[PDB]
Amino acid sequence: ETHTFNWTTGWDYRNVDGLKSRPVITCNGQFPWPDITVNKGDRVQIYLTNGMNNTNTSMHFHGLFQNGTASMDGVPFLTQCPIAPGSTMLYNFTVDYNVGTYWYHSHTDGQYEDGMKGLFIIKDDSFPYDYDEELSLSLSEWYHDLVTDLTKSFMSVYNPTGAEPIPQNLIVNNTMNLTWEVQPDTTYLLRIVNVGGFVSQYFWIEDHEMTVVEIDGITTEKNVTDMLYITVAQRYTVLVHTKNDTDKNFAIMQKFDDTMLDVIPSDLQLNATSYMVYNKTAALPTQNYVDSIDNFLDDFYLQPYEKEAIYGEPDHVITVDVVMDNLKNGVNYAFFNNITYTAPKVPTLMTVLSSGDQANNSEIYGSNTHTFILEKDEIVEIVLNNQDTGTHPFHLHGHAFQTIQRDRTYDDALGEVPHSFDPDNHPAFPEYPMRRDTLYVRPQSNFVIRFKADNPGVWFFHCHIEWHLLQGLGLVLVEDPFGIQDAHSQQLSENHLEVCQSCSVATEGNAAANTLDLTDLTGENVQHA
Ligand SMILES: *C1O[C@H](CO)[C@@H](O[C@@H]2O[C@H](CO)[C@@H](O[C@@H]3O[C@H](CO[C@H]4O[C@H](CO)[C@@H](O)[C@H](O[C@H]5O[C@H](CO)[C@@H](O)[C@H](O)[C@@H]5O)[C@@H]4O)[C@@H](O)[C@H](O[C@H]4O[C@H](CO)[C@@H](O)[C@H](O)[C@@H]4O)[C@@H]3O)[C@H](O)[C@H]2NC(C)=O)[C@H](O)[C@H]1NC(C)=O
Ligand SMILES: *[C@@H]1O[C@H](CO)[C@@H](O[C@@H]2O[C@H](CO)[C@@H](O[C@@H]3O[C@H](CO[C@H]4O[C@H](CO)[C@@H](O)[C@H](O)[C@@H]4O)[C@@H](O)[C@H](O[C@H]4O[C@H](CO)[C@@H](O)[C@H](O)[C@@H]4O)[C@@H]3O)[C@H](O)[C@H]2NC(C)=O)[C@H](O)[C@H]1NC(C)=O
Ligand SMILES: *[C@@H]1O[C@H](CO)[C@@H](O[C@@H]2O[C@H](CO)[C@@H](O[C@@H]3O[C@H](CO[C@H]4O[C@H](CO)[C@@H](O)[C@H](O)[C@@H]4O)[C@@H](O)[C@H](O[C@H]4O[C@H](CO)[C@@H](O)[C@H](O)[C@@H]4O)[C@@H]3O)[C@H](O)[C@H]2NC(C)=O)[C@H](O)[C@H]1NC(C)=O
Ligand SMILES: *[C@@H]1O[C@H](CO)[C@@H](O[C@@H]2O[C@H](CO)[C@@H](O[C@@H]3O[C@H](CO)[C@@H](O)[C@H](O)[C@@H]3O)[C@H](O)[C@H]2NC(C)=O)[C@H](O)[C@H]1NC(C)=O
Ligand SMILES: *[C@@H]1O[C@H](CO)[C@@H](O[C@@H]2O[C@H](CO)[C@@H](O[C@@H]3O[C@H](CO)[C@@H](O)[C@H](O)[C@@H]3O)[C@H](O)[C@H]2NC(C)=O)[C@H](O)[C@H]1NC(C)=O
Ligand SMILES: *[C@@H]1O[C@H](CO)[C@@H](O[C@@H]2O[C@H](CO)[C@@H](O)[C@H](O)[C@H]2NC(C)=O)[C@H](O)[C@H]1NC(C)=O
Ligand SMILES: *C1O[C@H](CO)[C@@H](O)[C@H](O)[C@H]1NC(C)=O
Ligand SMILES: *[C@@H]1O[C@H](CO)[C@@H](O)[C@H](O)[C@H]1NC(C)=O
Ligand SMILES: *[C@@H]1O[C@H](CO)[C@@H](O)[C@H](O)[C@H]1NC(C)=O
Ligand SMILES: *[C@@H]1O[C@H](CO)[C@@H](O)[C@H](O)[C@H]1NC(C)=O
Ligand SMILES: *[C@H]1O[C@H](CO)[C@@H](O)[C@H](O)[C@H]1NC(C)=O
Ligand SMILES: [Cu+]
Ligand SMILES: [Cu+]
Ligand SMILES: [Cu+]
Ligand SMILES: [Cu+]
Image 1 (cartoon, rainbow, N blue to C red):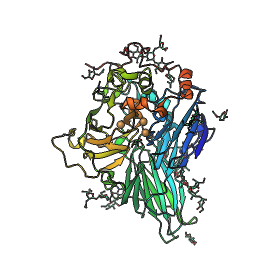
Image 2: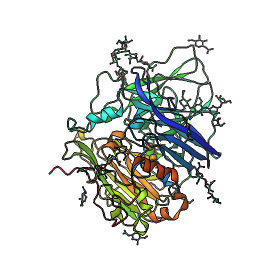
Image 3: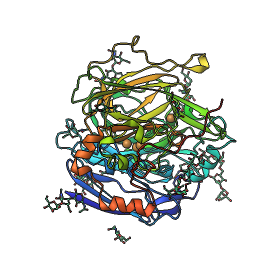
Image 4: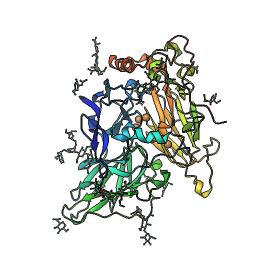
């Protein structure tokens, strides 16, 4: 079945918070943006039109593998060139390899924080568990200023610390103090999605246990908890069974991970209360006080319903250290090893599709682009060493990876230093590792993920904290470029080329005109020595 949408971006005032009428990004004049629900193997065709006066746009469908259709991933200068004001890009893709809970968001500057985001649900007939009803909750933080404005003082010489701007409130389904009307003795499938741009959240329901049955599109064995820690971009789908009494109402609770906040403003409501309503007439629940925020479920120990044994020894190991540092222009950037992601003059995919037999040479994709080439079916391992004292949720396009190590917090307040993964010295990896698309490193810690390069494409690996992505915390994976070239489904459509010309962005071979293919590029500001 084909679902066709016609959506146009725009700006309108809303008071999402309850406390500031403020421009938000609308879809055809409406807010919030719609949610898509399709069946396994359906076709989705979205005509996105940039109706904004002065920004570019894009749309990325988070978690979808885009197998055979990399062009549709929606990452400017990886997958497409940006959508210019007035232009219309057609996103045309099938959904043959994904099931469960996903979302879509703009992949331009900070755009999605300003409202351009929505849920994408794929149903399957073979979901193992029973439930009576189903819904979602979209957790997020909310700012009173647009990202464009915050960026001016975020990426600034008057911000040498790289301190990320502090949000004004937590929101659910684009309000505060939300009502969820329930029926007694009923099992609800509750999709909890963190569609925020920055802050991790703790989530729990007063006097109700939660049975985790899916993370990031991957069905899991039932795991019961009282509390979840959800980073931005991740999804926990959870079974909740309601009580027999219609006598009392219960608090739905979301809490900031204030650890991630540079400073805590004294008036910021760190924890927000919503309402699970059994009785429409009874007392609205007060805040549910919790004794500890240290006993949330560690998703590392989750067990996929479809077991896959840990992949064998890696053919390709990528080791990256994560740090924040100041450059020559005095502003604070984010680094994978010694590289801040700096967008190229020609989108990654566009150069692979016109480099012919030189697509295997890493040099042509640029030096300041952090591009790696992955071989036909090789097992790839990413080793990430956090040298920064914060938590980061890293996300990988095109794959759900195996999480084989994710070390403990190394708290610098207790005097502890950063620790890297040591291939010679580490706990035994799990036999059947957890799988997902978005995973956090703990402060000053490390993680190791593994996946098979079985999905020809161009895939972004980055921190999903919008501020850190703006700081350039990302790298590019090119999965067998020859596999990309050989597949017909992968060739760029007339519409996409039309977007590029309308944007005055080339489809050549990184800078140079398909002529020597050895560059004279676009670099990062030089180092501080
Ligand atoms: C859910 O329920 C919550 C709590 O009930 C509702 O939030 C309340 O909203 C009202 C109306 O928007 C707020 O009243 C306004 O208060 C401001 C001053 O606000 C400041 O001082 C407060 C007192 O300590 C403090 O609570 C505020 O903190 C909040 O805001 C900051 C961001 O600013 C945020 O980070 C925090 O997390 C808090 O949310 C804040 O520091 C006052 O200036 C307002 O305007 C008056 O004057 C002007 C005249 O120019 C006029 O426009 C108005 O009519 C008014 O006369 C107004 O009094 C109230 O502070 C909020 N209460 C709390 C405790 O947060 C929320 O709206 C509900 N959500 C929904 C339905 O979306
Ligand atoms: C926060 O925001 C999210 C949206 O982002 C809301 O999520 C939606 O919640 C509603 C329930 O409140 C869900 O609606 C239910 O969908 C079920 C399945 O979808 C079927 O229907 C459509 C038809 O176009 C097709 O996809 C296909 O037919 C599916 O089978 C239905 O079972 C429900 O249908 C209706 O009839 C039955 C009669 O038995 C009634 O019981 C229902 O109430 C209803 O009238 C129902 O429509 C919806 O799926 C959720 N969407 C998403 C994206 O998850 C949250 O509700 C909101 N949170 C709060 C508290 O407001
Ligand atoms: C949405 O719309 C487009 C999407 O691409 C953006 O417009 C482009 O912006 C980029 C950067 O964001 C521009 O790239 C820059 O070009 C500079 C000058 O190049 C011009 O001059 C030659 C002259 O022959 C032209 O051929 C060319 O088209 C340009 O007009 C470069 O100087 C910049 O790189 C580097 O400059 C300094 C100076 O030494 C170096 O030190 C650094 O390496 C630095 O990176 C840079 O590459 C591009 O020109 C813009 N227009 C296009 C492609 O038409 C919008 O920015 C975007 N809107 C927003 C903000 O959302
Ligand atoms: C949305 O994407 C799909 C996937 O490519 C497009 O469907 C395809 O459309 C093309 C041309 O419109 C079809 O090409 C035709 O192929 C036949 C043989 O199958 C050949 O005889 C013709 O000469 C022609 O080239 C292609 O078959 C078709 N595939 C499917 C799955 O239907 C679609 O066009 C895209 N755009 C739209 C309509 O929005
Ligand atoms: C936001 O949420 C947190 C967590 O719910 C709130 O902190 C909690 O505050 C309560 C009391 O205000 C603490 O309970 C105490 O527990 C001991 C048990 O030994 C008991 O003897 C005391 O009588 C008391 O009840 C609780 O520890 C504390 N939770 C944590 C993890 O610190 C916080 O107050 C909320 N923010 C608000 C409403 O301003
Ligand atoms: C449910 O999750 C828990 C942890 O959240 C897993 O059980 C234990 O987890 C600890 C770490 O706290 C590990 O040392 C062990 O794997 C378990 N310990 C005990 C008490 O035996 C469990 O694996 C999960 N169950 C699922 C997904 O079915
Ligand atoms: C969507 O509808 C608009 C009206 O806002 C119309 O102009 C356009 O043709 C439609 N989009 C596409 C590209 O089909
Ligand atoms: C709702 O709660 C009130 C007490 O606040 C009670 O009087 C009323 O009967 C309840 N409604 C039902 C039918 O559950
Ligand atoms: C850091 O990466 C390598 C390390 O040897 C070096 O060649 C390169 O110049 C540095 N990156 C850039 C281009 O800033
Ligand atoms: C891509 O499709 C191929 C062919 O069906 C399949 O073998 C592979 O597993 C797919 N990759 C992903 C990421 O689903
Ligand atoms: C690129 O992969 C090919 C196999 O297609 C192989 O010959 C070689 O090891 C790789 N070459 C480079 C330049 O890394
Ligand atoms: Cu995403
Ligand atoms: Cu993604
Ligand atoms: Cu980060
Ligand atoms: Cu991304």
